[PDB]
Amino acid sequence: AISCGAVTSDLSPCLTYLTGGPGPSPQCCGGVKKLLAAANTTPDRQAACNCLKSAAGSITKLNTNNAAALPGKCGVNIPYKISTTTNCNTVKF
C-alpha cells in the first residue's frame, strides 16, 4: 500500500531532473519504476498519484515536457500524464 513516504523517496532524486537539471538520474529511474510497480491496481495508483501530483506542485515552473521525458527516458512510460491539472482517478484500467 503506497502511503507517501515511499513516493517522496524517489521524488528527491527525481527533483534534480524535474527542476531542469541533469538526468534522468540512475537513482531516480529506479525509484520511479518502483512507484508504478508497487501500484498494480487502481487504489494503490490513486494514493501515489495523489502524493506525486501534489509533489510536483512545488516545482518552480514545472515542465510538462520534462515530466514526460523522465519516464520515457527511464524506459518506464505510464498510461497517464503528470501535472497539477491531471486526475489519476479518471484513469480507466
Image: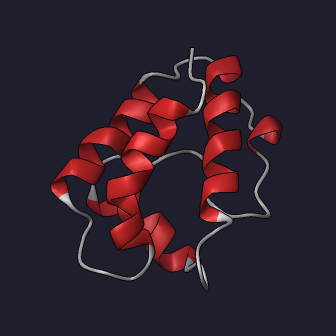
For this view, does 72 lie left or right of residue 62? Answer: left
Query: Residue at the location (60% across, 48% down)?
Result: 52
Q: Quadrant of residue 10?
A: top left
Query: Residue at the location (35% across, 71% down)?
Result: 17
Q: Residue furthest left?
A: 26
Q: Nearer the viewer, residue 77 or 28?
A: 28
Residue 47 picture location, percent across and down: 68, 29
For this view, does 63 lie left or right of residue 86? Answer: left
Quadrant housing the N terminus: top right
Quadrant housing the C terminus: top right
Residue 88 picture location, percent across and down: 73, 42
Q: Quadrant of residue 79?
A: top right
Q: Quadrant of residue 3?
A: top right
Q: Nearer the viewer, residue 1 or 92?
A: 1
For this view, does 90 lie left or right of residue 79? Answer: right
Residue 63 picture location, percent across and down: 55, 80
Q: Is residue 15 above or below residue 91?
A: below
Q: Is residue 76 above or below residue 40?
A: below
Query: Residue at the location (50% across, 46% down)?
Result: 78
Q: Is residue 49 above or below residue 28?
A: above
